[PDB]
Image (tube, rainbow, N blue to C red; front, side, top):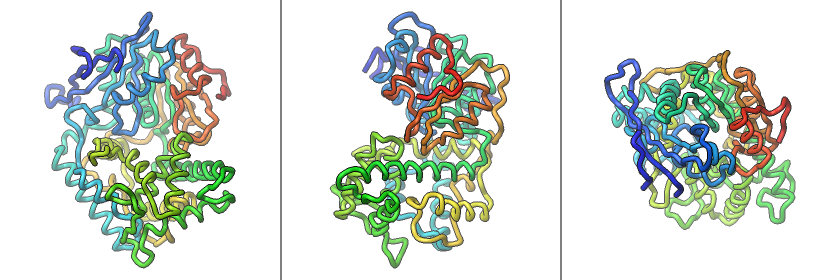
Length: 463
């Protein structure tokens, strides 16, 4: 890797070629983008991070993380982020939707699960999969999965001059981690997995656990807000879900589920029901955003939706010129190849039945007896991985950080990952998704000690 300064730190940027198909090593090539913040003291090696998603840029993440890196870590490690194959600055980038495509979807309430509804959604999905194949070709799409990102990660380790890998992975990044752990166990110096993905999970049950996670974060946010003056969800947290629906349900035409009646906003779009739900989900990643949710809901009381629109934009990664980054398109393409998709109609219909009961804050009206297949049921390229218990017997002891009320990657998933990995569980008591290098000096203390000294947290370490 020829490094160059970056066109906000001591930052150096560079590229790395990897083969698109590893079985055809001298074929098409991808250029992975890399950023590096050199260590200030005695360098142990590079701390390579990944934010997850998938579709999330590691370069962007390293820039953020840089501001909150502890001084002992920054002394001893190059902070290094990278964009996985097909993501962000890596070429070729995954793209399916135009900016207009994304906008057009987000304007729809996406709430009608009648047969006509389901046919509509499923038709949009086919057109989406078509735009993917059109712009990317089936070969690149076939090899964007974690199984090959794991292999890129070893190339990155090597290219960085490290004998063994020191890795911090958040969320989906914990899948990269455990995958790398299984293929290159003898190359792992240290590894922290914060916000855990259990590769052995049933996809449907995981989804339903994630729905439960967000409904509980909703419960927690609303109980908090109920103690506060002028809570837009009311002073009785047992009624917050209903009150929430009295605020968002009118964004859908009562006699016709397909008609959006958006709340007024300074932006031309206004706020659709779907964007209202998305912005809510976004705010529930972190208590840091609870104030914003409370603002967004107070706005709704006046038929305004500016803050919720801005939250959904944050989630959707839409800048203020209405341009999207490719994280949405990459996320799907990568998710779709990491496991076999659910194609059974009945299971999909049953999940919806169960989801409406587990997470009412998210569901609109009544169970209809029908539900759409996910985008992955229509993928033109087969899964390059498959659910299994992580098995990496000689793996160095790793640290899994799991948060008690994490809506995105629930606590138990952290427990199970640590189990399979035979590593350490460090609990964070909180209602948020991930926590490492995000202000909590206790967590950071354990993580610093593990990174430098190799010292794992004691059994039952809580923080």
